[PDB]
Image 1: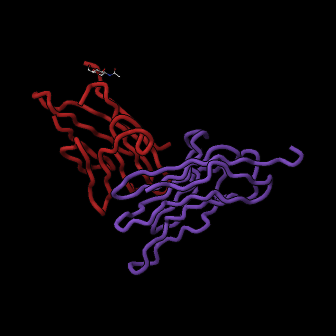
Image 2: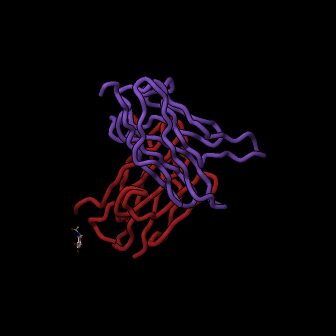
Image 3: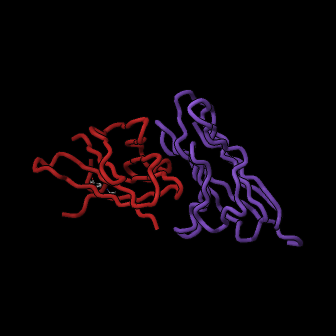
Length: 130
Length: 108
Ligand SMILES: *[C@@H]1O[C@H](CO)[C@@H](O)[C@H](O)[C@H]1NC(C)=O
């Protein structure tokens, strides 16, 4: 399997943009245990900016950019023993873009039995007249 | 801040058994543990073991034994490895995220 991400994503300052991330192709028997979004160049307490659990849903441990400006676009947690969670589309959305949001974002899938599969995307924040 | 410790030792007088140990000191339960020899998991290292708290344990060569240990930690035994080899452990935990550290045999 592989992580499909764009090498670069461009968004307007103060606007909203999406960071695509997919675990392709669908493989029967491959279980996604966790999705982790990281800013690997931000300090240790600020790296883990978003995570998604198949049962408990999303979390945003780092205050920067924090939950106020981050959201999962299509990740759906499980709804009991009937419906299985859908974490293959780990696309992350940033709202109210600031110049502090420019840089590298990593999208990692903690998969069983394959392991950790990760891709990286650089977010470019476009400043008006700049 | 969450911390991952890694310890690799030769714990037998026969001097023919690498023992890899690593644990996660955090605020949440572990969703997955990935162990790799040579480098970071999924980023250059060769996958050695994948551990899930419910779906079981997955291991590759040359892992003779991979198992869970107490207090959010695991242990690993190699068959027979070099003294300068690095072993990396990555813990994926909700809600704090993923954390990884690496270790090696201490000098004699
Ligand atoms: C590691 O040690 C072995 C045996 O001492 C040696 O052959 C090898 O070159 C060493 N590797 C490095 C990167 O120094």
